[PDB]
Amino acid sequence: KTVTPEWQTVEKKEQQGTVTIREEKGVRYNQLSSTAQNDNAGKPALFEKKGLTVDANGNATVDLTFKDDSEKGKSRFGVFLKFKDTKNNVFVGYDKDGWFWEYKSPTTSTWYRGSRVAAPETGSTNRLSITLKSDGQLNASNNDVNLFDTVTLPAAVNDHLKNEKKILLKAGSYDDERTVVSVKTDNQEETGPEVDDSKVTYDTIQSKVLKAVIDQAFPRVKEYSLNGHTLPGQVQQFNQVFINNHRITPEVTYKKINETTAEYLMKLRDDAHLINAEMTVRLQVVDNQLHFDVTKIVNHNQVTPGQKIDDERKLLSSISFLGNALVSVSSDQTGAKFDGATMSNNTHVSGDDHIDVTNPMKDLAKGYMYGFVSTDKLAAGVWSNSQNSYGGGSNDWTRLTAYKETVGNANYVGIHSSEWQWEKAYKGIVFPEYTKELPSAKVVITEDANADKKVDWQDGAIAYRSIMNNPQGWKKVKDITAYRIAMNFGSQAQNPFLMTLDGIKKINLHTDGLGQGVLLKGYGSEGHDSGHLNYADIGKRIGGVEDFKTLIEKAKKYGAHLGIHVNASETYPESKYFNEKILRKNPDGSYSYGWNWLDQGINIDAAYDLAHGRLARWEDLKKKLGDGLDFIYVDVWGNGQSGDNGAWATHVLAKEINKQGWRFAIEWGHGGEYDSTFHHWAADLTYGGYTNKGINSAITRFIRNHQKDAWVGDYRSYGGAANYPLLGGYSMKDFEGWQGRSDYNGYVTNLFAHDVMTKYFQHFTVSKWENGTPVTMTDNGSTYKWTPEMRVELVDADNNKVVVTRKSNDVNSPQYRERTVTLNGRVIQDGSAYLTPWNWDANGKKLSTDKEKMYYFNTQAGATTWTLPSDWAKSKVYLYKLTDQGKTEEQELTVKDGKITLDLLANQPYVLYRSKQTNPEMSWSEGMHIYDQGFNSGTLKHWTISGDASKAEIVKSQGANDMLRIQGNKEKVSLTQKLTGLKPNTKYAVYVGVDNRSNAKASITVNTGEKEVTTYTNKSLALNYVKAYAHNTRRNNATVDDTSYFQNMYAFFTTGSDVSNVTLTLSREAGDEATYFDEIRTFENNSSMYGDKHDTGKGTFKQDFENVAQGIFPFVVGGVEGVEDNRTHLSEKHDPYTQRGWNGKKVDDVIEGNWSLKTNGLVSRRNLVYQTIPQNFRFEAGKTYRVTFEYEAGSDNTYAFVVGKGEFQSGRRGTQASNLEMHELPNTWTDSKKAKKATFLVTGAETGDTWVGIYSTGNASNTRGDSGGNANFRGYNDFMMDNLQIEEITLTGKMLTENALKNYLPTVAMKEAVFNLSQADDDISVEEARAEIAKI
Ligand SMILES: [Ca+2]
Ligand SMILES: [Ca+2]
Ligand code: NA
């Protein structure tokens, strides 16, 4: 008997309730109760379970079954996640009035308005799921009912609770009322009507191999028979359908077209429900398949896609043959069994049902995705194109429904097609024709199909592949081994298109031609989460359409497939397609705001969007890009931001995308089961926790493992299916920016550790799946039982046979986590090492004999011996070490009676070949006008060095990222290349990224043949805080000593008519310390900032922001939010939406022209938002300048103009905030219709060291009674700059007193000292000036 509670009250004396163990009905519980000495505010009864705690990766999951034992309407229950205290937490729970979320923190505390799901009824049983992630993405469901739309915690709120690991249940009291809930513990230790065929007239259609007995009155199969064996269809007559969810007995006329084909015309009429249609069903046998097809529908009501309709009831919306089993099995038959699959993304809970059809037996009426019935002799499987959904979770994608039906002494289980869809409409407007897809289902019948001398669901599964749908593009999945995100954000152009080609080339070498998948996140507009919906708006700062086309063409040669990250759920005002009609509104007419980051977005009504030309937008992208693109990754879709993102809506989206020739990929793992080939939740193992991963179904994975990356990969933490799956499963990493990750070594290692074998298996189809003994595990706050897979067999078109076997059934054994793989009887993997053949090129084509190869990888040291196949056995054999320079350290191995022994470096890939091989010339950085732009070629030979060439060399950053370094040179060292492929008489920009730790001059110089422009830096003084950038200052990316001061150094120039002798020169003067360079980028640019001219030179400096090459030049982003997707960027005009007045917006996004420099929401941070650095603009020693700009600010004194010098807050004297010269700026709308103008006099410190910038003060903003998105959208918390001008002048005392006057007047309008300033002597000295101004 159990005396041990799974739950206990917390230790805080006053937050204590009463835990008690209670065993009632079948089940055991722990009853949590509140007491008299509790309340619902500071001192509620809190409870706590060992293990239940935010996971290593910062995701909180709760999956709690319970029942409410409180008096009806008297309960206040919920879960606290990431709990710090009563006023610092996230909460999901209910009260009288239903389910809500709520969060509390200094910055922001609110809860859920908007209609709630009703609270649980007393005693009813509740399966609660809650997820809070690292994104701050909160979702919850109760008994598979979504409780609310996804909420994302704001940056401020999430950052504060990021570290909190507490997960508590709350039970609150109020006066006499108490909360009492019983949580379900982990530990818990026939007749029916007979048939009457007397009036039925049957018929038979038959192929060579399959015969089906069919009714002449209604399209139903009585039985099938293959090779004398039988399976029933629908034994009892049911001559009724459901149209628009209404029961209707059709008027049917029948006609047999030929021996294989019969068809029925079916009239459907119900005046009371405005039904008046006819349809033609066709039943056809082909080989061993029965095809059920509605071949024609006619709605006699008048309906026209695109046109509005007066009464949605006149549409023929849904057709249901539910009640007619397409195939079934009888408990009278031997081996009677049904097996089905339902959606599960919980690594602990399989989604599969395995039911013996017996009499007696349990009720069965359930939706399924895949379904099979089998006897001892035959198996059948059913397919349907139904996009029915019975609900969320396991009720979704339920294209089949299985039913128990008692007929006489027999229990039948039959598989029916779920409801079909047809004419649908949104707010009266009928959807486009292409949304309609004629209903269709198929049955396949099979004898043994995997030669194990028994007939079960697996035999159905094998047969099922010839009737099922297949995700468009699925054939490519096998050979995409290296997926990766290349990211751009905030006008920064972190990963230009042509530059991505270098990374493709790099991986090509290190993997010896394995296939790649690069997802361009921020390909459009300014980057990621900018200009959503305008899919055709390829981003100009990363190379425009021209470069994106080049990237696609040249990537083919390396098996690099490209995709783009899009969003069909949300848009920002900047966008072209942004417009009030497309926006989503709540019942009360307020906007459904999306997330606030660069700008505050607004959700869109996807239904409206579909009804109003969304297809046009895909076709524009296609017209713009042309052929070449592989896939489209649709972010967000699934979270209900944009409304209905169900099976039906998702199918329609996928068809739009597919129709352009593109593959479909989604974020959601629940999502797009019918069409997707890639799910981020499945692929990125460390994200969302154990309940948000891939499809946990042996049946589904059996069927489709080779077609998509959608499965449960290896992640020991998550347990269950995730504890070393035998088929592996794609595990993703990256090094080109995503989530601040730019470490290259770990990318390749992971690739061989997990993905090579995962992809090997995808070159075969599963044919046998054998499970072992149930085993007990304990993780993520529970103890649960799990049946692992023990043996999987796969097969090939050419009869090759792979056999994967787990080396132990014992979960405590380490060999539980080990497998052996045999190819045709021969061992290719055992435990930590494998030696796999790989006989396919990057694009999956068969490699020619002479190019066939094997890969070796071993996660430990130690010798391993391998038997060679017959065609390698009597041969020479060469081992190569694979590095970022390709094949290295060639080594002839010794073969000994068909065996070789490898004793090599652990976690290092090697490739074996039958003959000597060489690496090819990569043509690095091609199209970028320079060779090896990022120093990946292992050599500086291409550079003309001048000086002591030993003082320059390529070195690796702390992120394994190659860089040029010059150091310890006692004389000038310089490296020169000629710029290639330039256009005559054309304006250009070039930058090299530079991080200079020496005071010595580090310079970039272009010489056009007609002119020479130069730009230089001394010791760098600005840390790099751009999260998506390779050389930001995170440890894993730091240059050296855990810091990075990398910033782009520019030179602007113009070619003359002769381009044959344009050279670029990086150089460094004498110094001991190091300068590091990386990433030389040269590109067309039409700015003119230097005395109204383009070329770098003397003259007044002006930035109107209209022709910025990249970034926020001459500023660089500061440390105000640490290394981050910085919330300062170039904002784009789209009038009226981005300007004053629209939706109550208080300030302009763009002050003049089409572009301005916008900061969003960074108020009250006490830190530098951005600053100049000397290499972008140098305030020269002793000279005085007049800095001038126009600006908008939505609150008084939230942002300030600052003059500083040296490295800000570097711990050196006077680099502190106090010591900056600071000018707080007032708001620009309360008393003005346009941006105000600022003027400052700045004199360069003698250390050549000075800079100016914008600082976020400690003052609070003033949102004028607004809040939420309204507050964000309207710019109370924003700051915009435009029309910068810096101009050298002659400092004089008078000059100072005049500028002071202008700066002190605004105070005077709400004195005598200031009047006296205005009549200061024309020749006041700078001293007396400062004297007087100080006294004001
Ligand atoms: Ca079999
Ligand atoms: Ca402008
Ligand atoms: Na923007």
Image: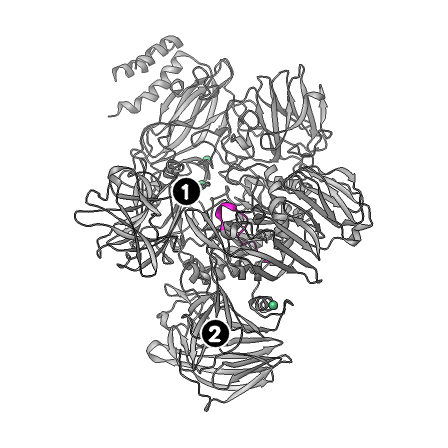
Residue 1306 is situated, as x and y percent measured from the top left of the image, at 30, 25
For the C terminus, which image quadrant? top left
Residue 1137 in sight: no
The answer to whether residue 297 is left or right of residue 894 is left
Magenta region, mostly helix, strand or loop? loop
Report crowding for label 1: few under 14, some 14 to 19, many 20 or more residues within 10 A (C-alpha): many
The answer to whether residue 996 is left or right of residue 361 is right
Asked if residue 377 lies in the magenta stretch, the reply is no
Residue 31 in sight: yes
Q: For the residue with label 1, is its CB less than 8 Å from the closest atom of ligand 3? A: no
Residue that protrudes farthest toward the front in the picture: 1
CA gap, disc 2 and disc 1: 43 Å
User: Regarding mark 2 in the picture, which secondary structure is present there?
Assistant: strand
Q: Nearer the viewer, residue 1322 or 193?
A: 193
- Image quarter for ligand 3: top left
The answer to whether residue 835 is left or right of residue 1088 is right
Residue 370 is situated, as x and y percent measured from the top left of the image, at 51, 65
Q: Nearer the viewer, residue 1327 or 954?
A: 954
Q: Nearer the viewer, residue 494 or 535?
A: 494
The amino acid type, in three-letter code, at marker 1 is: Val
Q: What is the number of the mark on residue 414?
A: 2
Total marks in image? 2
The residue labelled by disc 1 is 54
